[PDB]
Image (spheres, coloured by chain):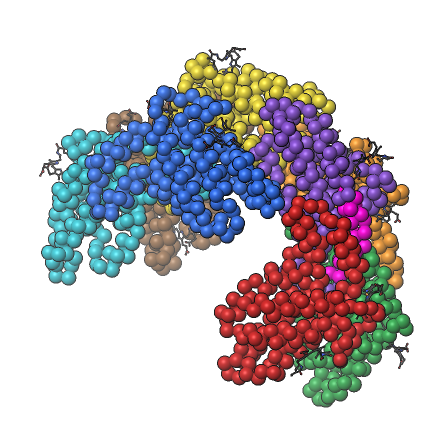
Chain colours: A cyan, B yellow, C purple, D green, E brown, F blue, G red, H orange
Amino acid sequence: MKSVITTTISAADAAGRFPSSSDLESVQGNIQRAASRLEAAEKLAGNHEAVVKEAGDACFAKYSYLKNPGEAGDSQEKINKCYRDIDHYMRLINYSLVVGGTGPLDEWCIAGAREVYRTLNLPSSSYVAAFVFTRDRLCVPRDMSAQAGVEYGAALDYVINSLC
Amino acid sequence: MKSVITTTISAADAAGRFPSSSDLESVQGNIQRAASRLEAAEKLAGNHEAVVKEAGDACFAKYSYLKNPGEAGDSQEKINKCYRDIDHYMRLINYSLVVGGTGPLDEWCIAGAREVYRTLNLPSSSYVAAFVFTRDRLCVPRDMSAQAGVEYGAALDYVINSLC
Amino acid sequence: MKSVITTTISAADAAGRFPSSSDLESVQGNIQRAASRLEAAEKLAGNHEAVVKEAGDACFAKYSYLKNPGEAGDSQEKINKCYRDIDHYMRLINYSLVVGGTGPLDEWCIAGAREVYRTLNLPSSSYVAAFVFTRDRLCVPRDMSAQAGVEYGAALDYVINSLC
Amino acid sequence: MKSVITTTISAADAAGRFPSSSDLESVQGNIQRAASRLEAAEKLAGNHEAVVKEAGDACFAKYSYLKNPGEAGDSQEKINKCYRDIDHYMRLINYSLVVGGTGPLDEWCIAGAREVYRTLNLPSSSYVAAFVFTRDRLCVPRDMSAQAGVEYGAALDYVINSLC
Amino acid sequence: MLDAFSRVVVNSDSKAAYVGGSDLQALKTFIADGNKRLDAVNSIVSNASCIVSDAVSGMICENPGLIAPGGNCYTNRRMAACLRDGEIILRYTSYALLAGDSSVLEDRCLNGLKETYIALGVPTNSSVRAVSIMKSAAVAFISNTASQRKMATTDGDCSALSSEVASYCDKVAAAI
Amino acid sequence: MLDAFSRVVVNSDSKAAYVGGSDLQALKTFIADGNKRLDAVNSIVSNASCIVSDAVSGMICENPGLIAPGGNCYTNRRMAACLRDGEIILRYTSYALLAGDSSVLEDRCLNGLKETYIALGVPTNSSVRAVSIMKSAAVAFISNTASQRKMATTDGDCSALSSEVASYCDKVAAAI
Amino acid sequence: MLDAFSRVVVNSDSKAAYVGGSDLQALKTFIADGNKRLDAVNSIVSNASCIVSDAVSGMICENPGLIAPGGNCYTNRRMAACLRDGEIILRYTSYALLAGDSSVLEDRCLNGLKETYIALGVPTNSSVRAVSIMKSAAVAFISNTASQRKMATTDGDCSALSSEVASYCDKVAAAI
Amino acid sequence: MLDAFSRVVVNSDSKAAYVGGSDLQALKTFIADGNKRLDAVNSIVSNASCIVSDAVSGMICENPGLIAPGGNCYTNRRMAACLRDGEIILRYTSYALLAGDSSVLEDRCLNGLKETYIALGVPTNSSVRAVSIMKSAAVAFISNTASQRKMATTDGDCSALSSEVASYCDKVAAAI
Ligand SMILES: *CCC1=C(C)C(=O)NC1Cc1[nH]c(/C=C2\N=C(C[C@H]3NC(=O)C(CC)=C3C)C(C)=C2CCC(=O)O)c(CCC(=O)O)c1C
Ligand SMILES: *CCC1=C(C)C(=O)NC1Cc1[nH]c(/C=C2\N=C(C[C@H]3NC(=O)C(CC)=C3C)C(C)=C2CCC(=O)O)c(CCC(=O)O)c1C
Ligand SMILES: *CCC1=C(C)C(=O)NC1Cc1[nH]c(/C=C2\N=C(C[C@H]3NC(=O)C(CC)=C3C)C(C)=C2CCC(=O)O)c(CCC(=O)O)c1C
Ligand SMILES: *CCC1=C(C)C(=O)NC1Cc1[nH]c(/C=C2\N=C(C[C@H]3NC(=O)C(CC)=C3C)C(C)=C2CCC(=O)O)c(CCC(=O)O)c1C
Ligand SMILES: *[C@H](C)C1=C(C)C(=O)N[C@H]1Cc1[nH]c(/C=C2\N=C(C[C@H]3NC(=O)C(CC)=C3C)C(C)=C2CCC(=O)O)c(CCC(=O)O)c1C
Ligand SMILES: *[C@H](C)C1=C(C)C(=O)N[C@H]1Cc1[nH]c(/C=C2\N=C(C[C@H]3NC(=O)C(CC)=C3C)C(C)=C2CCC(=O)O)c(CCC(=O)O)c1C
Ligand SMILES: *[C@H](C)C1=C(C)[C@@H](CC2=N/C(=C\c3[nH]c(C[C@@H]4NC(=O)C(C)=C4[C@H](*)C)c(C)c3CCC(=O)O)C(CCC(=O)O)=C2C)NC1=O
Ligand SMILES: *[C@H](C)C1=C(C)[C@@H](CC2=N/C(=C\c3[nH]c(C[C@@H]4NC(=O)C(C)=C4[C@H](*)C)c(C)c3CCC(=O)O)C(CCC(=O)O)=C2C)NC1=O
Ligand SMILES: *[C@H](C)C1=C(C)[C@@H](CC2=N/C(=C\c3[nH]c(C[C@@H]4NC(=O)C(C)=C4[C@H](*)C)c(C)c3CCC(=O)O)C(CCC(=O)O)=C2C)NC1=O
Ligand SMILES: *[C@H](C)C1=C(C)[C@@H](CC2=N/C(=C\c3[nH]c(C[C@@H]4NC(=O)C(C)=C4[C@H](*)C)c(C)c3CCC(=O)O)C(CCC(=O)O)=C2C)NC1=O
Ligand SMILES: CCC1=C(C)[C@@H](CC2=N/C(=C\c3[nH]c(CC4NC(=O)C(C)=C4CC)c(C)c3CCC(=O)O)C(CCC(=O)O)=C2C)NC1=O
Ligand SMILES: CCC1=C(C)[C@@H](CC2=N/C(=C\c3[nH]c(CC4NC(=O)C(C)=C4CC)c(C)c3CCC(=O)O)C(CCC(=O)O)=C2C)NC1=O
Ligand SMILES: CCC1=C(C)[C@@H](CC2=N/C(=C\c3[nH]c(CC4NC(=O)C(C)=C4CC)c(C)c3CCC(=O)O)C(CCC(=O)O)=C2C)NC1=O
Ligand SMILES: CCC1=C(C)[C@@H](CC2=N/C(=C\c3[nH]c(CC4NC(=O)C(C)=C4CC)c(C)c3CCC(=O)O)C(CCC(=O)O)=C2C)NC1=O
């Protein structure tokens, strides 16, 4: 799971080395930035359903043509999966904010995603629509602190940039 | 030059990745621990000659037999180089404290050192004597702050552990 | 076990070849030089204890500081192991003279020896002292024939050169 | 050029090693067997033309069908090359006896020989006929000493065994 | 590769000198602007796709001969090649920026690039139009003056950082 | 490999659940003891040579048959092999300790170790005497109760950490 | 691999003992018969092609089912495979003979051979008929009693050597 | 690589000639001095460590700029590099000496060395001061005139051998 601690340890393991100052400083940085990514993570976890629901509504608002027969929203089961996928992604962002790195996003949702969506006809743009909406929707200090806005917005940009 | 920043960047370069949260947190740790390793570094740089001189005296006090003919202290030029070597090592510790990692020690003095000393008959123990003396000699808060003592003592233990 | 016969056979095995003239000439050389290395080997085997004991006494005579607390001779058990190690080395020289090559020395005592001694604080110089003493102590024709002196002195120089 | 000296040196070069006892014993064997392979070599060099001529006559005696049109002896130029080839081989045996190993035979006449003869229709058996004749023709002590007979017969068996 | 501190140490070493007091205070300035630097890096990498296709589309925008038969962005295979190269250069300049040193840009990316391009047939006047567009896309994002997207940061002067990132882009435009 | 947070995330994931509030407060406790943990790791790695030759010398101390002909520390080559293995295990348990998870100890070091040893002939009752000595050398250094060397740290109870490092050493003594 | 002397040294070592006087005199006997041994090796290798196609032709001679469809010498490819294997085994037993030890025969040739053959389908009762024929072809040549070819050596009893070479051939016939 | 005999054979071959009688008697002279040659080789290799650190210490002795910042023996890493290179060259000249031909010195060690050094920055005037010191350390040991160590050999004139070993050292000093 990519993270400060794992990245550093496995650099040292590759070299045969005990941990040294670089490694301990790296974890210390994990301590400093802990307190605002965990804030984002808790706000996200506490309101996941409303965020997921605004994001999916924004997606299908931008691409109403998806509800046509043959598109990826031509049935209520299919639209509901769409919001499910968005929730999966936001759960993984929650994980990413808790770990401190993009590990969870990377392995659990980015990896097969271009092939899977190419094959089930899921336009990349619709997810980008849902994450861009969420990103721009966030409000400081209403929704969370400034440096937690940074962390949250950041994971969202990462997931967006994996679909470009 | 091994360090938080270099270790992280080259983990990401190996992966084809832009910097991400793990990387930025890692540098943030470099910022936090900066202020006490630079304190050690400045105290060391400001009093290098007296430290080098007590360490070399301690070495030749522990191993007076080195001053015998055939040993590595059988001439004034040779004893003077001994203190020179100790100074080289403390300069590299200065570098190590400024960079934030053991890079400078690693490349510039550890690498050839077992072969070189095996070949010029320089007992490993004498350097260990000089670094152990310096380490135990340090005094908090007299000589430096507590977390700078940690950094200084640490680089010294690293260089000691490279001669065992 | 490195030796004329083994070196030649495994050159031929690497090439897919039956033995040929080079190989048979090589063994013939083993026959010619047999009779003086076996002489050294038998003289060494017949007086191993006195040689081991003069060598260890010479070592601790040259480095009396080893008997200090903390050194590798600070206890009777430790000094006794020192003479034991010297005996191990002379047993391996016995093997080396019987095989005809440095095989036994190579695998059974050279291989881990720098790491082991680095870690148990055993100065390389002390063994060099003991082997140099033995080498210079040998006397022709008193102690053995001239071409056996050559063989014996040679294995000793080899083991010495593995500690430089 | 494969030989005792070259085989040993390049075993040591592969290992990073200075020459040691195995290597010096190997050369010593080269010294011992020198004096009878050089005897063979000088007798061969002193009577090469008569040996080449009896061998080629024996070949074309055994395989008179080679002189038919279409065979490898259908012209005087072709028969003359046949004796030339036999001479090449005996020159290489001369080299092999002087070097002490099969090097010269190996590189200079064995290497391309199956392809070359397959392509110019030169039956392998005819050369085998010529070398077997020479081998069986040798007479001790008339033609050379016993241990030189061994060396000469040996190179001939080697070249024979390269055509089976 | 080196960073800001390793670079000070290499220079100190060429004189066999412990790190000057002047150099230490420079480094503590580096440390003081640590967090602005992280925001700088974050504002480039969060927009990397924007920056790279802006620049390549623009390169082609100003010279459509690149996408006529025989131009180096002609097939899909070459277009995708160029997008990858834009992305790679941007990645090595974001390493530079996060490092405080151009060490890694020069070592791992620019070394032999000019030759490679000469060999392949890659127009160099065009690569640098792209890189110079990326330069402006990037210093915009750093300085938070990009037209169609903002990034909430605290109020300060980030101009030294922008100049840094532009100096690394110019190192690229010069390597070829 | 996983660390403390990745481990909480893997467990949350098996239920398809965002990270519980209970788990978040556990993690902020982990973060609160961050600096004690770093001192723990520093006190092991600064003494690694001590710990490893203490333990191997002790193993041989209690059973000199290991260094009689046919014992597995007999030649210099095998003695040096054993010292390397002591050092390696200590390295993977210092990774564990710095990680907060035994993930890397189990994955990169213990997996197949029992088999490898069975194959080589490496006495396993002895490996674990060594590992159990390393266990005490290490929790001494953590707890700052080592006889011949102290390490100036601030006054606190480091007992949870010591128990952690002893649990990783016991994972080793159990893998074989 | 070991030879006669290395083998004496390994045995001496298992007792931590310098080489006995009894062992030294055995070795000087080995050295005394050095030149007979070289003639032994020379008489095998100078006839290797004879020995290997004698044996394989004979194997097929006594059991023509090997060269009927489905037999393991059926195609040219399998026949040539078998000739190579005959040659290889003879080579490793001529290494044994020149070495004075079966170390290299067992290590580099026989180890896993039985398994390999079981896997491929190579009849083992037939491999050993071939190897047992090679045994006699070889001890003939050593003892200089081969019908159609002699090799001028001096008059002596080479029987210990012949028995040696037959013991190595039997090691082969037993490995499968 | 070639040795003394292979070298005579290559020269004979360029004329398609069997080995002259003159050449045979030269070779039997080579054989006559076989044992002196072995003593020559033994006197170098038994002192190799002496010869190599004598020479490198001396090189640095006469020009201490090598171990000032920027000199090529400056760090421990470069000093150890130079010691290895001294050792390597001495090894290839002891191969030459044991071979009777400079074939292996030129082929496996000197070929491209000049280029490699130019590339690395290795001072060539200094490499050859070291090699020229090794030359004298070596011909001393051969001729048994070394100050601080003797080697009991029988009384004879070993001057041709010393000149040989000095000619190989000069081949090195010339390759760069
Ligand atoms: C680049 C200049 C920007 C311009 C466009 C501007 O007008 N304001 C700007 C940026 C800026 N940031 C700070 C201070 C902080 N930046 C922070 C985030 C980074 N530090 C981190 O650890 C992380 C990654 C893990 C970062 C992305 C933080 C945490 C701070 C400090 C407190 C805060 O602002 O929330 C300043 C100066 C303000 C200061 O106190 O230094 C400026 C100008
Ligand atoms: C392991 C328990 C130790 C026992 C033996 C004890 O009696 N006191 C102990 C350790 C301990 N350390 C702290 C707090 C700190 N430790 C620090 C160093 C580590 N933090 C880092 O960033 C680095 C590496 C880069 C470390 C090596 C630091 C900086 C602190 C905080 C301030 C300080 O103490 O100097 C505590 C608790 C004190 C606290 O405020 O947390 C204890 C018990
Ligand atoms: C294997 C037994 C043979 C039987 C068939 C027999 O009736 N006579 C036999 C062989 C035999 N050879 C010797 C002695 C020598 N063999 C020599 C050649 C080998 N020594 C070498 O260096 C080389 C290769 C390079 C060999 C091929 C040599 C040189 C000798 C010694 C002198 C000589 O005979 O020419 C003996 C015993 C005679 C003795 O003095 O040992 C026997 C029985
Ligand atoms: C290099 C010249 C030396 C100078 C310094 C000198 O005054 N005497 C010298 C050397 C020398 N050695 C011999 C003859 C021998 N050298 C022998 C050992 C080498 N032969 C080997 O097989 C081995 C390795 C396995 C050697 C190291 C041997 C055995 C001899 C022959 C008999 C003996 O001297 O013990 C000579 C000439 C004397 C001669 O009869 O050739 C010289 C001058
Ligand atoms: C893009 C802005 C350029 C414009 C101008 C254009 O018309 N074509 C452009 C780019 C381009 N680059 C390649 C092929 C390579 N580029 C290479 C260098 C990059 N590869 C790296 O790993 C890195 C970083 C260290 C760099 C900077 C290399 C190497 C190649 C060759 C390998 C390959 O993928 O072909 C091409 C394609 C040329 C062709 O026809 O193959 C183009 C069009
Ligand atoms: C020693 C006498 C020289 C003096 C003069 C000096 O100031 N530095 C010296 C030597 C030196 N050599 C290297 C690095 C290499 N040397 C190479 C050639 C050797 N490597 C071989 O395998 C052989 C035999 C065939 C030769 C003769 C090669 C190759 C290298 C490069 C590989 C390496 O280990 O670096 C250096 C270090 C230069 C640096 O900064 O890396 C020095 C100082
Ligand atoms: C054809 C002439 C044409 C192309 C297609 C573009 C080339 C170009 N882009 C320049 C600057 C630039 N690009 C970006 C990223 C972009 N802007 C946003 O707000 C966001 C979001 C994106 C994604 C599309 C930025 C931020 C900038 C900054 C400068 C600016 O004026 O916007 C540019 C200027 C180069 C220069 O300064 O010389 C060019 C030529 N632009 C075209 O006109
Ligand atoms: C033979 C019976 C014998 C050997 C040689 C040792 C084996 C042993 N060591 C134990 C614990 C231990 N080792 C260290 C490191 C050591 N102590 C220091 O202060 C420093 C510095 C070093 C480097 C030498 C430590 C810190 C400890 C901690 C515990 C202690 O009592 O010191 C140990 C105890 C294992 C157990 O608790 O069962 C053994 C058996 N010890 C020998 O007696
Ligand atoms: C079919 C039944 C048949 C085959 C084709 C042969 C198998 C066989 N060979 C035996 C022994 C053997 N082979 C050689 C090599 C051969 N003899 C020479 O003189 C020369 C030259 C060559 C090259 C062809 C030798 C030397 C020997 C020695 C023993 C002998 O009697 O000649 C053999 C006997 C095995 C046994 O003892 O049980 C068999 C079965 N032989 C056939 O009859
Ligand atoms: C600095 C000026 C200085 C260094 C350190 C040395 C350089 C040097 N050595 C020369 C020759 C040489 N070295 C050895 C090996 C040495 N001598 C021994 O007896 C033993 C044992 C060793 C190991 C230390 C030998 C044998 C020689 C032979 C020649 C001699 O005079 O001893 C040397 C001379 C080169 C020349 O002839 O131009 C130099 C410059 N010497 C120093 O003075
Ligand atoms: C991590 C998960 C996080 C999100 C992201 C947001 C997402 C979000 N914001 C909302 C609510 C909300 N947010 C804003 C924005 C806004 N208002 C201001 O004063 C400033 C200047 C602006 C910041 C740009 C407005 C104006 C509303 C009310 C408008 C509406 O809800 O329709 C609502 C509706 C639920 C509610 O009313 O509370 C959601 C779901 N909430 C979260 O928990
Ligand atoms: C990074 C470089 C750093 C070093 C490391 C030290 C090293 C050092 N300490 C000294 C000086 C010094 N240090 C102590 C130790 C001491 N005293 C106490 O009150 C406490 C309880 C003890 C801490 C264990 C004593 C007792 C002395 C005076 C004794 C003496 O100098 O002989 C001196 C002599 C110079 C002087 O007198 O100032 C040196 C060189 N100095 C440095 O700049
Ligand atoms: C392979 C194992 C081999 C060794 C190596 C030696 C080692 C050795 N030499 C001794 C004995 C010994 N050796 C010499 C040397 C000497 N005398 C001369 O006439 C010439 C010119 C000198 C050659 C340089 C002297 C002078 C003595 C007597 C001095 C003494 O023993 O204290 C002794 C004492 C035991 C005894 O007295 O016999 C030993 C142990 N012995 C061995 O078996
Ligand atoms: C290395 C190069 C070497 C060769 C190989 C031989 C090859 C050889 N032998 C010959 C000559 C020769 N050789 C023998 C063999 C023979 N006679 C005996 O007393 C014993 C018992 C027999 C050993 C088996 C006979 C019988 C003759 C005479 C028969 C004849 O020449 O026609 C001849 C004819 C030239 C001559 O008459 O001198 C040649 C060419 N010569 C060499 O220089």
Q: Which residues are magenta?
A: C23-44
Which image quadrant is residue E93 in?
A: top left
Relative to D72, is E129 on the left or the right? left
Could you say where residue B123 lies in the image, as x and y percent from the top left? 63, 29
Q: Is residue G58 magenta?
A: no
G139 w.r.t. E3: above or below: below
Could you say where residue B152 lies in the image, as x and y percent from the top left? 47, 23
Determine the residue positioned at 35% across, 28% down.
F159
Can the viewer see residue E162 in this picture? no
Determine the residue positioned at 29% across, 54% down.
A112
Determine the residue positioned at 34% across, 30% down.
F160
Total labels: the figure holds: 0
Q: Considering the whole magenta stretch, tell me its main secondary structure.
A: helix
B131 w.r.t. E131: above or below: above
Could you say where residue E18 lies in the image, as x and y percent from the top left? 51, 22
Determine the residue positioned at 62% across, 77% down.
G56
Could you say where residue B57 lies in the image, as x and y percent from the top left? 60, 17
Relative to C71, is B6 on the left or the right? left
Q: Is residue C41 magenta?
A: yes
Q: Residue furthest left?
A: A76
Which quarter of the image is occupied by the N terminus of chain A? top left
Can the viewer see residue E70 in this picture? yes
G160 w.r.t. F117: above or below: below
E87 vs H88, nearest the viewer? H88
C120 vs A53, nearest the viewer? C120
F138 w.r.t. D9: above or below: above
C163 vs D105, nearest the viewer? C163
Relative to C140, is B121 on the left or the right? left
